[PDB]
Image (cartoon, rainbow, N blue to C red; front, side, top):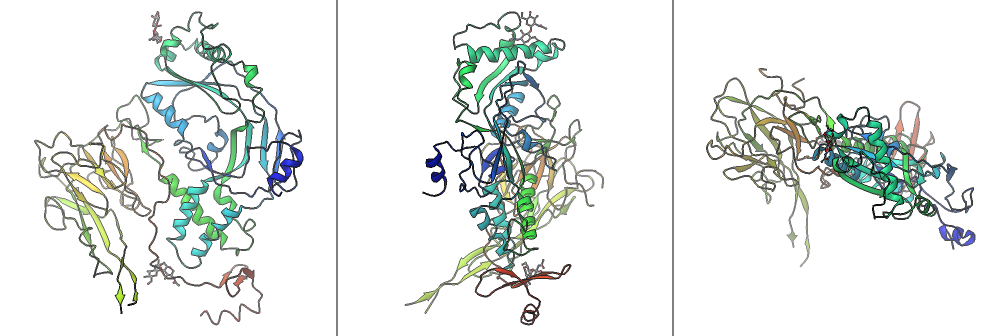
Length: 604
Ligand SMILES: *[C@@H]1O[C@H](CO)[C@@H](O[C@@H]2O[C@H](CO)[C@@H](O)[C@H](O)[C@H]2NC(C)=O)[C@H](O)[C@H]1NC(C)=O
Ligand SMILES: *[C@@H]1O[C@H](CO)[C@@H](O[C@@H]2O[C@H](CO)[C@@H](O)[C@H](O)[C@H]2NC(C)=O)[C@H](O)[C@H]1NC(C)=O
């Protein structure tokens, strides 16, 4: 009777299913959430009179069709097109080199070029139909507004670390962007993975390699599965043998099946439209005082910074620097940003061992946290490096833990305390000159959220034994040289978001935050908003499957160990405006100059 169905019964038309306004994760090219409010109250149609659109949506009829007879050769996977999200991946931003590189299309493309030494060629029929954009005058959604009125309450009850936790669930549900224009259409793509040596000799006839790749596309679609082709003349007998992989996908329209005339495919584009391109803006662009009218002025510029910080923390994590050049040695497969760490010489370093101390700040009774958090060296004894080494700091933070008393008088009431314990986690560095023995070996780390790539499980190898360093992490270590020399990998040092390692620039801003030359860096155990890394040189830690995207949240949910401070008056000093909250938690109205002076006396 109201909403969509009133416009749909009166008009008898389909609804356009390619709509903007929704969110967009930009690492994994997936769509999620609904940021903008789409209401169908005026019963608008497209100017064709064929679909039904929302009110705050205007369409531009493209009615365009592209048909190319040549494939485009896309070697060197570091710069690639996405064919569905090319306009939103290549924005001018500081993280343009990480966009798109966790989507499902990229992790397939990167694997087939390294595991086969291949290049890729796509050929496509584009069929762009509309361009669907949002108006500038537009309001936020009903559910997206509610979760910004919860970030702005924790920031005014003086609860940081809970407002950071809710701004990292905001990015989990609504992505990093908001699509502001989509493109309803339907492509038809064929990707081939040719062998890379097949292109190097055909420098002149590279225009004939692609001319047969675009003719093998049209014989696959037009003729049936039975080979009645017209392309097998001279060179489409090595081309069939030099290829390593082939697939054909369709994005809109009727489902593709091999042998369907290109006439018959293009008559199913109607009523089956998808976004074959999209553009967008960042997520914190839409947190501003004219999208949120009832909140105060400078309070939504602080929500916009808390949500901006959680997007930049989701791109700083999921960034793997390493040697990207494929023909070189020290090629890191998991790396998705070039570091310049190729062609470097390595130096074998020896490390003393890690240790850790606890302090047990608050809850000295009923919970004893300084047993689980404490760890000694395996080769020294107490909390110290051995004789020829030196300690560095690497991290220091607080481990909270809730418990329960129960004071019975039968009536009983229970009190919920919290027990804190600050832990400091050192590691040792070879100072001047150490002989070849008298040092622990290394067998890789494994956290509780990860695995050791020596044994492909959460376990140290044979002969090795773990020792705890950051309340979940286990460093596999053995002191032997006959039975533990098979699983030993050379070690380059820990560093963090604060303290870089001193093993770069030898014989020594403290230092840089990177590995020495020839070593690859790997993340291990993000521990409350700061990640610690470690440098190795194996090639076994390098290989394997590509890592999935590490989704937020990264902080554990806090234990509410901070009291709330009720804020009433909000002001800025530079234009003399004030927003006085009324009684019984109603709203934020603007402050008249006769009531704020009567309200500052009860504050301070
Ligand atoms: C607002 O919250 C912050 C964060 O907890 C408080 O800052 C800390 O307060 C404790 C209380 O003694 C101090 O020990 C810390 O040194 C403070 N940290 C910093 C960085 O200042 C702050 O006190 C709270 N403000 C109010 C009015 O409650
Ligand atoms: C991969 O491509 C190479 C071309 O770079 C093919 O090598 C040629 O194959 C033809 C087939 O008769 C020979 O006559 C040529 O002498 C080969 N060499 C060159 C330099 O052209 C190779 O055959 C292809 N791979 C497969 C498995 O067929």
